[PDB]
Amino acid sequence: SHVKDILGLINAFNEVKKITVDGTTPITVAHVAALARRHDVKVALEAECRARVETCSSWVQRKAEDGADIAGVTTGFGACSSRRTNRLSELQESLIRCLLAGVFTDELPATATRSAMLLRLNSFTYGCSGIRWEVMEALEKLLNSNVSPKVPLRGSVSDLIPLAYIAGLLIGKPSVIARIGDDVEVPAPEALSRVGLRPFKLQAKEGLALVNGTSFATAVASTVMYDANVLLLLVETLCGMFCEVIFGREEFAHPLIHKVKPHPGQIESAELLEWLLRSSPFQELSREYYSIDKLKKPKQDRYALRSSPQWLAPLVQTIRDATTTVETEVNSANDNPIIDHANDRALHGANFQGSAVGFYMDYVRIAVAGLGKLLFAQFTELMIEYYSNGLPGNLSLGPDLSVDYGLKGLDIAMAAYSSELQYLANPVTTHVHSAEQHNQDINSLALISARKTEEALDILKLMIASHLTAMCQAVDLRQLEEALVKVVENVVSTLADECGLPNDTKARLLYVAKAVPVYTYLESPCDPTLPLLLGLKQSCFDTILALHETDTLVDRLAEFEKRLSDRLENEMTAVRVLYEKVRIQGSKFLPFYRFVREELDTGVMSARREQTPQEDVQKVFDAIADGRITVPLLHCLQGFL
Amino acid sequence: SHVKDILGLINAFNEVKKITVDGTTPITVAHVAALARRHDVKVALEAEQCRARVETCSSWVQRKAEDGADIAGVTTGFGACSSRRTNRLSELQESLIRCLLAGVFTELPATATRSAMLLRLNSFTYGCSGIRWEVMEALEKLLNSNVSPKVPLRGSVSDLIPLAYIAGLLIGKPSVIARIGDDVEVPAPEALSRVGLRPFKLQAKEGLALVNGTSFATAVASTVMYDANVLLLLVETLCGMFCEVIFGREEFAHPLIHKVKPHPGQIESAELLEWLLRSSPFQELSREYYSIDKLKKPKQDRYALRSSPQWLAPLVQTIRDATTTVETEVNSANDNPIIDHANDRALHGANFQGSAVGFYMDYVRIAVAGLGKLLFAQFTELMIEYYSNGLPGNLSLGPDLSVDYGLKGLDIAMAAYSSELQYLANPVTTHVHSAEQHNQDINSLALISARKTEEALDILKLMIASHLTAMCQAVDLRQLEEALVKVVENVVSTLADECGLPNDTKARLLYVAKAVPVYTYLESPCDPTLPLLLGLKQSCFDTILALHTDTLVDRLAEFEKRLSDRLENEMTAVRVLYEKVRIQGSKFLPFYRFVREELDTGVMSARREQTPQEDVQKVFDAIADGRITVPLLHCLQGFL
Amino acid sequence: SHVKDILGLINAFNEVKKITVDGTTPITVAHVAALARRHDVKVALEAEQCRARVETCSSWVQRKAEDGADIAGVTTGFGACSSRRTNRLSELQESLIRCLLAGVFTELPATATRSAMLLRLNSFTYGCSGIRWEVMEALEKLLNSNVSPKVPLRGSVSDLIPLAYIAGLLIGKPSVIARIGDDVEVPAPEALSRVGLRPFKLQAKEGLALVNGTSFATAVASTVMYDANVLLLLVETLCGMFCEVIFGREEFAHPLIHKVKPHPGQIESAELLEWLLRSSPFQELSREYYSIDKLKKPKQDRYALRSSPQWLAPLVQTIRDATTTVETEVNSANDNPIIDHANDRALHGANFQGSAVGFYMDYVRIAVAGLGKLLFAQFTELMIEYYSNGLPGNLSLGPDLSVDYGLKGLDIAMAAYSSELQYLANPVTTHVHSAEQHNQDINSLALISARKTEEALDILKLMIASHLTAMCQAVDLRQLEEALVKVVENVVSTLADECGLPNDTKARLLYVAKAVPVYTYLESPCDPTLPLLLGLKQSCFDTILALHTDTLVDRLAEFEKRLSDRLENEMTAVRVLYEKVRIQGSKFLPFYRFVREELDTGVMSARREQTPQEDVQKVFDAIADGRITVPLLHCLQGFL
Ligand SMILES: *N[C@@H](c1ccccc1)C(F)(F)C(=O)O
Ligand SMILES: *N[C@@H](c1ccccc1)C(F)(F)C(=O)O
Ligand SMILES: *N[C@@H](c1ccccc1)C(F)(F)C(=O)O
C-alpha cells in the first residue's frame, strides 16, 4: 500500500543522520527534506567514486587542451556553439559572468539553495561531468557548514542563472553575497575564508558543469513531493475523523465496492478508512442516531464523505507517481555534454532539460487543488446544521448564539483558500516561449511550476490546520451532546415519576427527550417556541386523547411543565460548565484530539474561551509546518497492515 | 517498451471481430475504439459466464424491494432526497428518468453514444446492478443493429442526463429520437419495433442502474486514449524523420545519455530514435555537411530535436498511465448501490464518481499540448533558413521565390493550432461547483474534461498532418539539393578544363561549388550578387595573387562567360527531371511513399496546382481514419 | 442608461431593411447581426458616396506598382519575405492566395462568413486599400445572393487563411466550394456563373487587400457583442423576477445605496430593478410573509439577489465598452499598406492586427462567466427549501414527492453549465507564439478568442432558458401556495366553530394555519408528524392548560379527527383546479404569458407528460431565435 510507503518516508525523514553521496546509493525526497530542514543532518561524500570523478576531469582537461571539439568546452554556449576557442578557462569565467543576471526584488530560500547544492553534488558523483573532486569536497564542506549564496527568485526556464550563484560562491566572486546560518551575510571570498576554503579557478568544462543542471527545480520539487506525501496521508486519515464527527455511515469504505472499481488509490484509501472506523465508538453513536426516526433521515451521506475513496484515487496515484519521477531526476547526471571517458568521447544531448519534473509539477498542483476541494466540501457540511446531523451551525457552542458566531471566520477563510488554490492549479508548462536566440525552442519551466506547487501546498497546510481544528471542536460538541441528552432524559424520567404521570405519558415524553436534537434548544431549553417544549406539548395533547380522570391528569401535566422550567436548565448548565472546566478515548483519532487539546493546550471554542480562532489554528498550522503532526499520525496508524 | 504496447493496441484495433462481454475478460481502449469506428465489429454478450449472477442479482433486488428493505434509490428518493421512502417501486424508477430527460439541443456523436452503451452493458456483467438479463440482451441487440438515441452534448457533472437517453430508448419514450444507422431517425418506440423489441417496464432499481454510471465520460476517454497512444507513437517516430531532413546529429539518442537520466519514457523514446537513425543515408549527408567549413557551423542541434527524448518522457508516461486508469474504469461496476447478494447487502458508496477519469483527462490534455509544442518548435526551425542547414525559407522550391511563398500558410496555421491547444490544456477539475441541493459537493466533471482532451487531439491531428507534409517536402528538397550540387560541381570542373585553368584554380572553384548552399542561389545561379559567383570571384582574386597573368585573367573571364552560358540550363534540366535516392534507404520510406504515391501528391511549387489544403487534407484524413498506421507499422518492422 | 442603449440595439436589429455601406455611415453590431440572421436584409453599396475615392486609390496603386514604386506586398514579398522585390504584379497576388488556401476540414458557419464579407466590403469603402470598385460590387452581389465560400474553422492568428477562401471564390478557384442558400454547394466557378459574375484576375495589391484584414475575428465578435448585450439585459431584468418568486426584499435596489457607491453599471442595474419591483403584487406577498413570525426569519436576503447590482456593475461596463471597441473595428480600414493617394504615399503599418478585438473578447468571456455564476447562485437558492422561503425542494409540486424530483435534472445541468463556462473564460491572448518565421512575434489570436466567447454565450443561453423555466414554475407554486393557505384557514375556521371551540382556541389554530409553510405538509396534510398537525397539537394542549374540561377535550378530539374529513379533499380540489392572480399585476407577466401561453407549457409535475427537455427546449429556441425580445421589450415599456 501507498500508506506503508508514506509511513516509510516519514520514518526515513526523522531517522536519517547522514546523507551518503556516492554515485550508487539513491537519495530520496525524505533525504532532501531532512538535509533542508534538520541542520544536524550531514552530507558524507564517500570516495570509495572519487577515482571515476578524477578519470573524468583528467580526460576533459587533456582532450580540451589537445583541441577536441566539445560543446561549451572548446565551443561557445547555446545558440553560439559555432564559435570555437582554445581559451579554456576564460570561456568558463565568461559563462558565469554572463549568467549572474538575476535581480533582487524576494529570493530562493536557503532551504532550496542548500537542497540544490546537494543535488548538484549528487549529479557529479556519476563521473560524467568533468568537475574536479576538490570542487565536490568544497560543496560537501559548504553544505555541512551552513553556507549558501543568496539567490534571486526568478530567471530560470529550467537552472542556469540560479546555479551561477553557487558557481559564483565557489570562485569567490565579490558581488556574490553568501549566507552562513540565519543572519550572517558576507561577500563570497570571506564566506569561503570563514569555513577554511579558498576560491577556485575554473578549468575546462567546470563553469558549465556547475550551471548545466536541473538542481533548483528538482530541489523544490523534492520538498514539494515529501510534503505532498505527508499531507495526502493526513487528508486520507482525517476523512475517517470526519466520518466520526458528521455521523457518517462507514459502509462507504466496504472493500467490495472498491474491489469492483479497482483503481489502486481507491482500494488503498478505503482499506485505510475501513480499518480506522472498524471499532469506532463514534460509529456506534451514528448507528444509534439513524435508528431514531429512521425514515425521516438520509439513507446515505453526502459526497464529501461517501465519495472520498473515489475522489482520492487519482490524487494518491498522481502524488506517488510524481515522487518516483522526481527521485529519478535527483539520481541523474543532469548535465551536458556527458563524458563517456571509458569510450573516449563526449556525448551531446540535453540532460539539463527539466521536463519530467516540470510536467509532473503541473499534475501534482491539480491533485493538490483536488485535495483542497475535498477539505472545503467537508468543512462546509460541518458548518451547516442542515447537513451536520445535530451539530450547531458554525459549530457554535453558545448557548447564547447571538454573541457566538463560532467558526464562521474560519469558514469564510476556507472559501478564500480553496478559491486561490484552484487558480494556482492552471498549468505552467503550457506557457513555453521560444527562448535564448531561439536555441531553446522547447523549455521545461520546471522551477516556476515547482514554485507554484509549493505555494499550493502552503495553502493546503492552512486548510488542513482549519479542518483539524474544526473536527476537534466537533468531537467536543458530540461528547457534550451525549452528556446533555442523558441529563434531559434523566430530568424528564424523574419528573414524570414525581408528578405521577401514567406510563403512556412517560414513554412519549422520554421519546421526545431522546429524539429532539439538543443543540436546537440549548439556547433556552424551556422556551415554549423551541423544539423540546414543542415536542413535549404535542405528546401531552396526544396522551390526553389516548387516555380520555382528565382534570387530575391535566393537573399533573401542568405541574410537570412547572418543575421542568425550575430544574432542567440548571442541570443542563451544570453538565456543560463541568465539561468546559468518553467516546474519543476509544477512537483511532484519540492521538489527534489529545495532541491538539493537551499538547498544544487548546479547548472547546466559545465566548468564554479568550483565545482567538487565529491563536488556536496557528498552533495546529505550526505543528503541520514543522512536522510535529506526524507523531499523532503515526500513533493513529499503529498496527495498520 | 511502451512502443510494443502501442503496436499491440493498434494490431488489436485492426484485428478484433467480436468484443466479448462476460464480466471477466477485459475490454481495452482498442476494443472500444474498434466498436465505435468499425461497424463490422460485433458485441458478444456471453450468457454462460454471467447470466446466472445477473439473474441472482435482479431477483434479489426485486424480492428485497417488495419486502420493504431500505435501499437508496430503490425504496428511497434520489441524491439529496434519500430520506423519503416509498413502496412505489416502478413509479420511482419512471420518475427518475422523467426528471433526467433534461438536456437541450442547441449533440454527442453516435460513436460516443454506442461506446457508452457498450460500457453500461459491461458494468452490468459484474452482477452488482440488479438490472434484468433481458435488458442486457436488448442493449446487445441495439448495439449490433446500429440503433442509438440522439443525445444532448451537455448537462453531466459525471453521467445521469446523457445515460437517461439510453434508458429513454429502452422504455420507448416518444420524445427520445433514435438513429438507425446513418440515414434513419425515428422516435424510440418505432426504433424498438424495427429491431423486434418492445418497451421495457422498469422494475426496482432498473432506472437508477441504467443512469448511475460513468459510461459517457469513459466512452469519450477511451477513444481519446486510443488516439493519444497512436498519435504519441507517431510524434516520437517523426522526430527521427525530422532529424533526417534538418541535418541533425543522431548522437542525441545515444543510450548512455539516457541511461544516466533513466526516466522510462526518455530511455524508450531514445531507444526508438537510435534504431530509426542507425546507418541512415540522410545522417550520412548530415556528416558531410558538418565536415564542410566545420568550425563555422553549430556543434549541437537546437532543442526541438536534441531535447526530444527528455521532452517526450513525461508525455509517454502520462499517456500510458492514463490508459491503465481509463481501462480500469471501463472494466468496473460503476453503479450505486452495489448489490452483494451473496451476503444479503446493498452497499452504499459512490462508484458513479468519474474522478479517476476526470483528473487523468486533465493531465493527458497537458501532455497533448506538450506534444503540440514539440511539433510547433520543429516545424518553425524547418521554415527558417537560418535554422534549417541549407533548406530554403518556407521550404519554397521556387526557383522564382517572388511567386512562391511555399508553406508559409501552413506555418501561420501551426502557430494558431499550438496557441489554441495551450489554452485548451487548462484544467476542468479545478472548477467543481457544489451541485444538486449541495449533495454533490465534490463532482468529477469527467465528461467535460474528456470532451476538451478530445478537442485537443483534433488539433494535434492537424499539426501532425502539416508536419508530415512539410517533412515530405523537405525530403524532396534534400534529394534535389544533392542532385543540384553534383551538377554545379560537374559544370565547374568541366569548364575549368575547357578554359585551361591551373590545378590550383580548379581546386578552389570546386570547393566553392561544394561549400555554398545551393538554395541561396538557385533563383539566379549566375547573379554576381548571389553566393555562388561571390565565392567564385573571391577564389579568382586569390588565385591571381597566388600565381602572380594577362592570359590567366583572359581565361578566368572566359570561365565566367561560359558559366553563364551553361550552368543555369543544366540546373534547370535536373530540377525539371526531378519534378516529372536517399529516401530509398531510410526507415521513413513507407511514410514518404504513402504520402507521395498512395495519396498521390508531389513536391510543392508554383507549377503544382494543388493547394496546401488539398495536400494536407489527404494526410489529415489518413491520420483520422487510421490508414496512417500502415506506414507506421511498416516503418517499425523489426524494432525490438 | 445602458438599458436604453440596448433597447436601441434590439429595435435596430428588428427594424433595419438595408445596410448602407458608404464609407461614412457607421455599421453597428445590430446591423451585422441583422445581415447574418435576416436574409431579407440587403446590402446597399452607395457609389455616389465613395466610388470616386475607391477608383482614385486603385488607379494610384496600379500606376505606382507598374512604375516600380517600392510597396510591401505589392512590389515586394509578404511578411518575413518583404526584402524580395518583384515586377510580377498579378502573379505575386495569385501566389499569395495559393499559399493561404491552407485550412483543413476536420467549419465557420455561413452567418460568420457572410458577416466577414460585409466587413471586408466596409473596410474597402474608406479608399485606402487599392481594390477595384468592381470587386466591391461583386461582394455586394454575392452577399445579396446568399453565396458564400465554405471556410475551415482554424488557422488564423488574426485573418489571412479564412479570408483567402473569400478571395478564392472571387477568382474562381476550383478547389473552393461555395454555398448558395441552405441547400446547394458547388465549386467556386459555377457559383460565380449562377450569379452572373466572372472570375476576377487579381491586379496589383488586390490579393493582399482581400486577405489582410480582421474581418472574421470582427464578424464573430459583432454577433457575440449583439448577443451579449441582449442576454445581459435579460439577466438583469430576470433578477427582478427572481426577487418576486424568492420573497426578496426590494430595498437592495434602493437608489441611495448605489448613489454612495456610484459604479455606473451598479446605479443603472439598480435603477431598472427598483422600477421593475415598485408596484409588485409579489413584493406585497413578501412583506406579508416576513410580518408572520418576523423574528424567526432572515432580516436580509442572500447575496445572489441582494448583491446583484454590485455584481452586475463590471459586467455591464465590460459588455458596453467592448461593444464600442468592436464597432470601431467594424468601421475601420483594417488593411496594409494604407494608401494615402492624396499625398502620394503607401503607409506601412499594422492595421491587420486584431488586438483590440482579441483583448476585449477575453474580457467579455470573463464577464459572461460572471453572469453565469449569478444565474447558478440564484437557481441553487430556488431549488433548496432551506433557502427558498416556503417553496418546495426542487420546485416539486408533488404532492407525492417520492415520485416527483421536480427540476433536479435541470439543477444538475446548471452546475455542469457553470463549470464549463468558468473553464472557458481563461484568456486566449496570454498564448501568443512567435509566428511566421518570427515576423509575427506579437499576434492577437482574436478569432480564436471570439470563438471561445461565442461558445460561452451558447452556454449562457442554456442557463437563462433553465432559470426562466424555473421561475415560471415558482410563479405557479407561489400562486397555488396563496390559494392553498386560504383553504386551510377556511377549513380550520369553520371546523373550530362547528366543534364549539372557544374564540381564543380558534384564533391560535388560525394563526398556525397562516404561519406554517403549506409545502411542508401538502404531501399528507393530516399526517400527525408533519408541521400542520404538530402546530395544531401544541395549540390544543395550550388551550387545555389555559382553560384548566371533558367536553372541551371531546370537542378538541373531534376537531382533530374531522380534519381528515375535509381538509385533504379541499386541498386536492384547489390544486387540481389550478393544474387545469399575482402575476397579472406583475411587470414580469409578459414573460410568464410567453412561456405558458405562447410556448404552450404548464406547471411541471408527474401528471404533466412533457419532459423538462421539451419545456426548456421551447424557451431556449425563443432565446436563440430572438423571439424572447418581444416579452422583454413589453416588460420594459415605459422605463425612463
Ligand atoms: N544548456 C545550454 C546553454 C545555453 C545558454 C547558455 C549556457 C548554456 C548548453 F548550450 F550549454 C548545452 O549544454 O546545450
Ligand atoms: N448518484 C445519485 C443521484 C443523484 C441525483 C439524481 C439521481 C441519482 C444517487 F443518489 F443515485 C446515488 O447513487 O448516490
Ligand atoms: N500581414 C502580413 C502578411 C504576412 C504573411 C502573409 C501575408 C501577409 C503583411 F506582410 F502582408 C503585412 O501587411 O504586414
Image: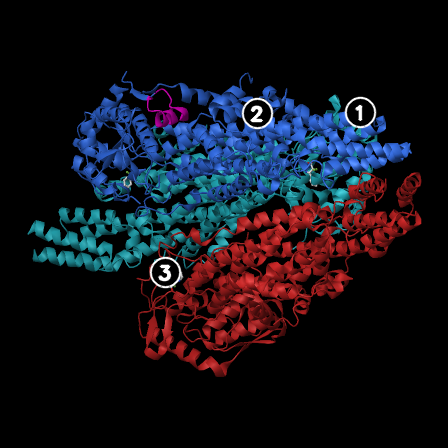
Chain colours: A blue, B cyan, C red
Question: Compared with residue B136, is residue C96 higher up or lower down, i.e. above or below?
Answer: below
- Amino acid type assigned to the residue bearing label 2 in the image: Glu
Q: Is residue B265 magenta?
A: no
Judge if badges 1 and 2 mark residues of a common chain. yes
From the image, tell me which residue sits under label 3. Answer: C79
Percent position of residue C151, x then y: 53, 60
- Amino acid type assigned to the residue bearing label 1 in the image: Asp
The nearer-to-camera label among 1 and 3 is: 1
Assess mark 1: CB under 8 A from ligand 2? no
- Residue at x 92%, y 48% (from the top left corner): C500
From the image, tell me which residue sits under label 1. Answer: A497
- Residue at x 83%, y 29% (from the top left corner): A505
Badge 1 vs badge 2, beta-carbon distance below 8 Å: no
Which region of the structure is painted magenta? A24-41
From the image, tell me which residue sits under label 2. Answer: A268
Instruction: Please state which of residues B42 and B370 is positioned toward the viewer in this rendering.
Output: B370
Q: Quadrant of ligand 2?
A: top right
Judge if badges 3 and 2 mark residues of a common chain. no
The nearer-to-camera label among 1 and 2 is: 1
- View extreme (bottom): residue: C48
